[PDB]
Length: 125
Length: 125
Ligand SMILES: [Ca+2]
Ligand SMILES: [Ca+2]
Ligand SMILES: [Ca+2]
Ligand SMILES: [Ca+2]
Ligand SMILES: [Ca+2]
Ligand SMILES: [Ca+2]
Image (cartoon, rainbow over all chains, first blue to last red; front, side, top):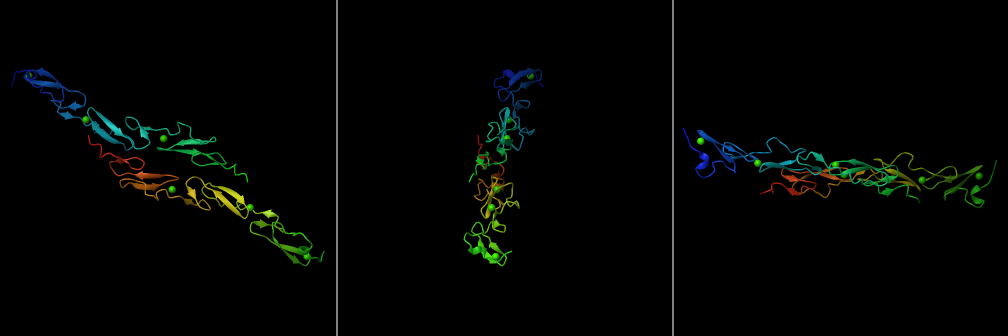
């Protein structure tokens, strides 16, 4: 069959607050974001297409995914390698190299270590 | 010429406290470590043979050299890459990888970041 407005019997036949739209012989559901199926029964797996980059963990949530980034990465898809050289950390005209969740200073001659702190022209004795 | 004991005239003809040994027609100097030359005049350059490894700075000193190591290296010749994994820093059965003046933790599934602190099996909600 059958001629009836399924949207007017009582409870909403569409799950997860979808909008019920009557048709002749059936009905249709206008689903909210993140829900699928004839009656919006399914919570879509937003992680199914592997959106999280750089070995991030994908969290399948309500109408969205969340990425948990590997250290040193950021962004919605963990697509951004954080720039550790942004604060220009190298002393004495050292050159900063960005790495993963860290930086490297390329010190000029006569200077060492991590931040080029040690003056070796200073070894005056 | 000439017949004379150069070691008995007065001052020591050998520099840098070398031992004066008389010979017929001359004399010879028995130099202390780090000195060379007929009269021990020269302070040997202990850095001449490039003893300092891994881009270390060589200091030419009295009868010895000293190496100034690049960060993460140690030893007389800076030949030792310091083992940062010695203290077993990785939490939750993470695997430690030794690097230069740093370490990397290879976390098992469900754990992140530097020391594998973050439990993601814990994202219970
Ligand atoms: Ca109908
Ligand atoms: Ca979902
Ligand atoms: Ca970076
Ligand atoms: Ca003599
Ligand atoms: Ca010397
Ligand atoms: Ca190391």
